[PDB]
Length: 126
Length: 136
Length: 139
Length: 121
Ligand SMILES: [Cl-]
Ligand SMILES: [Cl-]
Image 1 (cartoon, each protein chain N blue to C red):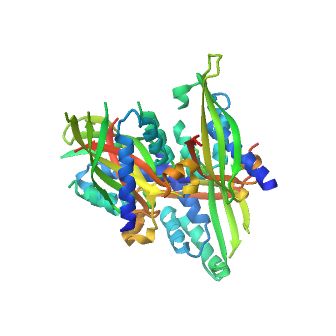
Image 2 (tube, rainbow over the protein chains, first blue to last red):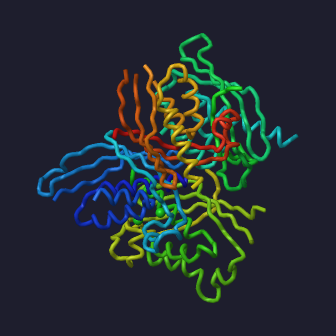
Image 3 (tube, helix red, strand yellow):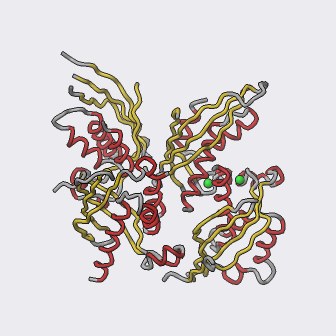
């Protein structure tokens, strides 16, 4: 369905924003994560604060009631090695809902026009 | 009355589709749940198959509807048994009893796809579905 | 895969923005079509709210056309098909018709947009052809 | 607030029901967890379900928006072994008519846990 397509896109965007490490996009990624997170999950993410980690989304299963499961890989390279480096696999378990986009900043609403908000997020090894 | 007959038919069709596991009806059962559900309930059902490659065609769970009570104001209660047999075997398998409580309405049927509107021209639509064990 | 998810998201967002007529979301819809479209396609949409013909002048606040997305199939080679319903009523159920949008699309360099556009569309989704035909079923 | 008093009570009841091990009450406890759980969380609990362990609630902090943190101890049985834990619990309230009559007698306010995770302290 369309609501599923929607949720799968934003769950995927969230994991990419939150799990990537890229020096030159990190301020932008950090900001994106706050704009897609509820106030308390945003406060909780802020409290966890050259290599490059890239994310591959493998699959996403929303339960249709505000939990989603995202299987994904992270590939961490020392920038100044040749290959793609070490790849590990993970499962994000993500609570989320949609808020009134008027109830956020104007900038937040441009980044997050549907008002998608992660309310909880946990990552476990696959 | 006619609303009661209509509602009782659909509640039972919903429980049968949603609670049956049979490899040879599965595609049809799966599509019926989709046509008859809100997107959230649809996805709630469908997400358990995103179970069939766990069970394949070795397990069959069939439903027996025991009573159907529409409770007024778009809620209905369906008592039913589910019976699971490994597909090899004669024997009765294991039977458990359940109560599905079901929030439902009739939506604009024009919004649905072609095939959905043939099967569900009245727009039966489940917005909440919950199964609890049978007690008193 | 992820590309399918991305494509299907943007294809539907496009059809919702472009086919919806709702006074209270019109300014946002209009702007979203602009961000997601080629100059041609953008002006093709925008042109219907210009001159004395402007659709909003001739509807105002008294008509609402809402969209239900029914299926989205990316067809490969940057073409996608969105089946959808449009439901119009003046402010019962109003009038529902079914439609097929065929959409040529690509991902362009996202720096070429105003920074507003790049916040909303950082991947650079860009529609270069848009056509709606009536639903006929299959055969 | 009252909403907080309410949430602390049901969150504490949930952890008591879900983390206690008592042979003579295990079936009632199992049933209680189902009646206090969303449909999906009830399915998930039932799958993962496979001495006497008693629960002591130490504190309950709801965030006011559907997440609660419960710090608690489990004591298995002189004294026995006590370990310490943190349940992170998502929850909401649903219309009590959307559940069975029996469910609704155990859970009159329609409290539903939508997610549950326990971590060591
Ligand atoms: Cl959004
Ligand atoms: Cl984008």
